[PDB]
Structure formats: C-alpha cells, structure tokens
Image (cartoon, rainbow, N blue to C red; front, side, top):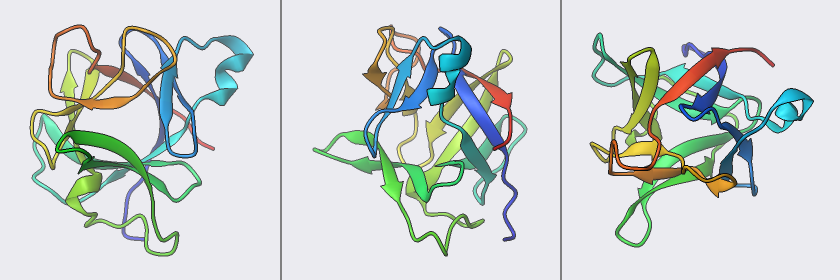
Amino acid sequence: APVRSLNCTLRDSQQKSLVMSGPYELKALHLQGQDMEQQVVFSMSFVQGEESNDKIPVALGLKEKNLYLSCVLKDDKPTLQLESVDPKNYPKKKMEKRFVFNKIEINNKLEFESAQFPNWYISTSQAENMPVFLGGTKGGQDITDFTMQFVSS
C-alpha cells in the first residue's frame, strides 16, 4: 500500500513496442495502429534503493498481474526473467534486489540498469520478434534506451 506506482508503456529508441510472448516472456516488435493493443502496460513502482537526480530505483511489474521483471543468474549469465509473486505481498517499497532497476534519464530517453548486476541493462534487438533481455553492452548494436508513455488501465 505504501508504494507509489505509475502505469506506462515503454518503446525502445527504434520505436519498437513490447508485447507478451509466452507466459513469462516479452518480445519487442514494430507495432502500430489498433494492433497496438497487444502492447504491455507496466506498473512502475518507486522502491527503496540509492536514489539520485539521475538514478531512480524502480520495480517493473505488469499492470494487473502478479508478474515482475527480475534479474537472476541462469547459466552463470545475468538474465532477465518474468517472475510470478504472491499477489498479496506485492508491490512493496522494499522489493528484493532482483526486482530493482535504476531508471536513468539520458537525453529525454531512459535506461534501466539492473541494481543486482551493475552495468547490465534491459535490452532489445535491432530485429523484431526477438525477446527482451539483459545486456552488459551499452552502445553496441543492441538497444538499451527507451521512451516512456504515461497511461492507465
């Protein structure tokens, strides 16, 4: 209850929208028009962590589902996953580190760094219908910057 949330959608800098692939996967694809319906709405929560003018810790859950983006090791590799949680205990202000991302504002765009694995960012691929992932390479050919749209649902 003592958590401030905010509904929104994310679009990568290449203007791709995010959509639920499997029950636990997000995909980024060029979506437009009415078809923009298969687009995911997040509830962004301002949680506890080391706040700053340029870094704001948030948790990213799907709007009315008990599903959260979390960063864990899977094969020794930092990996982004959708994690289901107790729908009674979430969201909360002191989320577990896995669930926390630092939101960074860069040139009217956003980057989400994993608080658990520093310098690892939520990333999308140049190509479409590719899954959203955790990447340890800023710049490069993979996209780590986003734009956010305020919404509601």
